[PDB]
Image: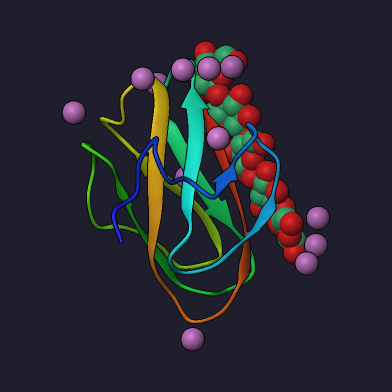
Length: 92
Ligand SMILES: OC[C@H]1O[C@@H](O[C@H]2[C@H](O)[C@@H](O)[C@H](O[C@H]3[C@H](O)[C@@H](O)[C@H](O[C@H]4[C@H](O)[C@@H](O)[C@H](O[C@H]5[C@H](O)[C@@H](O)[C@H](O)O[C@@H]5CO)O[C@@H]4CO)O[C@@H]3CO)O[C@@H]2CO)[C@H](O)[C@@H](O)[C@@H]1O
Ligand SMILES: [Gd]
Ligand SMILES: [Gd]
Ligand SMILES: [Gd]
Ligand SMILES: [Gd]
Ligand SMILES: [Gd]
Ligand SMILES: [Gd]
Ligand SMILES: [Gd]
Ligand SMILES: [Gd]
Ligand SMILES: [Gd]
Ligand SMILES: [Gd]
Ligand SMILES: [Gd]
Ligand SMILES: [Gd]
């Protein structure tokens, strides 16, 4: 389903890893700078930001920089991932 401020199921804290699964809809407040999505589980994942960048990918071995994500509350849908994985959202 859709992902947004009405049905997010997890909230990410800046720099704090959490277990993520395909289908999750994650709230993340970016106060400034550029969004970063990082994972080291080796599980490939992809994301859509509501009203924002689409088709973001991460190999599971480092950080994906997402230019042009708004400051403020973001809603990030995990579109694809083969299994649960540990991920963190950050900004700098
Ligand atoms: O502050 C003003 C100034 O900020 C600059 O922005 C900086 C920012 O402040 C830094 O935090 C950021 O640094 C990040 C590093 O680039 C990145 O390499 C590092 O990534 C770590 C990750 O945090 C860590 O979790 C991960 O650990 C994994 C191990 O590698 C694996 O062995 C193990 O299995 O799994 C663990 C995780 O469970 O390691 C990676 C490295 O491999 O994260 C840093 C943030 O925490 O850099 C920014 C600059 O590049 C900004 O640039 C300036 O403009 C601004 O003025
Ligand atoms: Gd709520
Ligand atoms: Gd850890
Ligand atoms: Gd775990
Ligand atoms: Gd920058
Ligand atoms: Gd937008
Ligand atoms: Gd990098
Ligand atoms: Gd908002
Ligand atoms: Gd808010
Ligand atoms: Gd808030
Ligand atoms: Gd699967
Ligand atoms: Gd770990
Ligand atoms: Gd910072």
